[PDB]
Image (cartoon, rainbow, N blue to C red; front, side):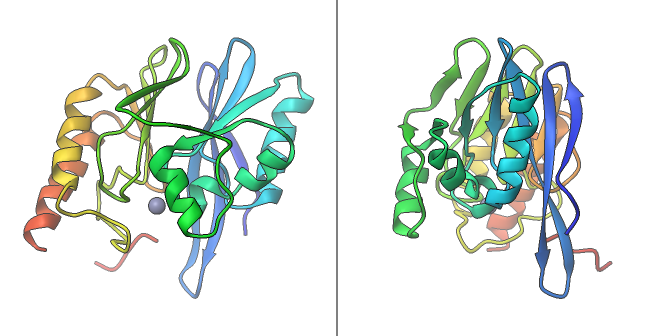
Length: 223
Ligand SMILES: [Zn+2]
C-alpha cells in the first residue's frame, strides 16, 4: 500500500489520501481533508487505519497546529477508521446521531460527540456539516467550508457510478441529491471519496446518476 499523502488544495485546506487494497483488483485511494482554522487543525474524515491517523495527526501537531477535532462523513471504515485512535488520545471526534447508531449496531467504536438536524456548525463561520438525506448510506453528510467555498462530498458524490449499493437508499438518493445541488451550487471545489476533485458540476452528475439508478432499479475501468 502506498504511503499516506497530504496535498495542498487551498489556503489552509489539504487533501489527505490514504489507500486500501482490494483483493486482486488493486489499490483504491480515499480522500479526506485537513482544514486549518484559527491556527488549529480539523480532520474531515479519518484514514482507514490507526497507523495512518496517527501519522496524519502527528504530522500537523508536531509542526505547531493542534488537532482540535475530527468529523466523519458516514459510518464506513474509510471515514471512521481513525476514531478509536483519536478517542484514545482524547481528541474530540464528531459524527451524526445516525452515524453513531450505525457504528454502534456494527460493533464499532463511536464518536465522542454527536449532532442531528439539517445543519451543524463544527466551527462557527467556518466548518458546517449538512445532511442532504439518505443516499450512498442512510447517514451520509457533507462538509462545507464557506471561506473557501469548498465542499467535501465524500461517498455521496458519485459522478461515474453509484458503486456499492449494499447500504444505499436508491429511492431517496435523487431527492437528497437535488437538495444538495440546490444548497451548494455555489461551491468552487467538490471533493469525492475516490474520484477526482471537481467543480460544482459534480453535484449535477451525482443527481443524474441517482435518477438513472432509481429507474433502472472500487472503480470499474472495463469499457
Ligand atoms: Zn461509504
